[PDB]
C-alpha cells in the first residue's frame, strides 16, 4: 500500500519469492481441527490487586 | 367414624404419584444448579 506499481511489485516477488512446489501436498492449504466453545469460567483471585 | 375414609385414601394416592413425580424433578433441578460447585476445581498459585 502506497505509491507503488502493482506490476513492479508483482515482478520483485517472482524474482525473490522463488522455489516451486512439486507434490500436491505443498499447495494444499490445510484445514484446521475445529475448536470447541464451552460456557464456563476461570477466576484468578488476588485481593492485593 | 370417618365418612371421608374413601376420598381420603383416593387422595393419598394422587398425593404419592404427584409427590413422586415432583420430588424427582426438583432433585434434578437442585443437582443441575449445584453442578457448577460440585464439578468445580481450584488451584493455589503463589507467585513463588
Ligand atoms: C363425597 O364424595 C367424594 O366426591 C369426590 C369429588 O369431589 C370424589 O373424588 C370422591 O371419590 C368421593 O368419595
Image: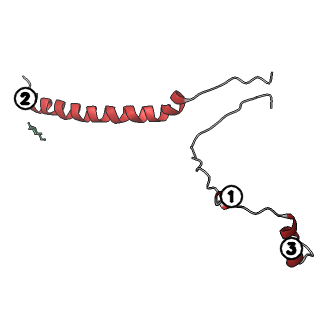
Nearer the observer, A29 or B31: A29
Q: Residue at horizontal 37%, vertical 34%?
A: B26
Q: Which of the pair A24/A45 is nearer the observer?
A: A24
Q: Percent x, y for residue A27?
A: 68, 61
In the rendered view, tell whether residue B45 sits above or below residue A3.
above
- Quick one: SS at disc 3? helix
First in sequence: mark 1 or mark 3? Answer: 3
Provide the chain ID for the residue under circle 2. B
Instruction: Describe residue B43's horizontal placement relative to residue B16 as left or right.
Output: right
Ligand 1 has an atom within 8 Å of the beta carbon of the residue at disc 3 = no
Q: Within 8 Å of ligand 1, the CB of disc 1?
A: no
**Which residue in the rendered view is the most extreme toward the front?**
A22
Q: Residue at x 17, y 32 (%)?
A: B13
Element under disc 1 = helix
In the rendered image, residue A26, in percent from the top left (x then y), is placed at 68, 58
Location of residue A13 by image quarter: bottom right
Q: CA distance from mark 2 to mark 3?
A: 105 Å
Q: Quadrant of residue A31?
A: bottom right
Marked residue chain, label 1: A
Total residue callouts: 3
Q: Are marks 2 and 3 on the same chain?
A: no
| Quarter of the view holding residue B9 | top left
Q: Quadrant of the N terminus of chain B?
A: top left
- Quick check: B37 left or right of B12? right
Depicted A35 relative to depicted B2: above or below:
below
Q: Quadrant of the C terminus of chain B?
A: top right
The residue labelled by disc 3 is A11
What residue does disc 2 label? B3
- Label 2 lies in ligand 1 vicinity (Cβ under 8 Å): yes
Residue at 8 percent across and 25 percent down: it is B2
- Is the residue under label 2 in contact with that under label 1 (CB below 8 Å)? no
The residue pinned by badge 1 equals A26
Amino acid at each position: 500500500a502506497g505509491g507503488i506499481s502493482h506490476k513492479e511489485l508483482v515482478d520483485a516477488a517472482r524474482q525473490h519469492f522463488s522455489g516451486v512446489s512439486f507434490t500436491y501436498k505443498e499447495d494444499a492449504v490445510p484445514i484446521l481441527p475445529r475448536c470447541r466453545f464451552t460456557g464456563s469460567e476461570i477466576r484468578a483471585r488476588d485481593d492485593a490487586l | 367414624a370417618e365418612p371421608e375414609h374413601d376420598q381420603r385414601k383416593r387422595m393419598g394416592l394422587k398425593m404419592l404419584l404427584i409427590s413422586a413425580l415432583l420430588t424427582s424433578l426438583l432433585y434434578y433441578m437442585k443437582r443441575h444448579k449445584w453442578s457448577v460447585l460440585k464439578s468445580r476445581k481450584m488451584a493455589y498459585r503463589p507467585p513463588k
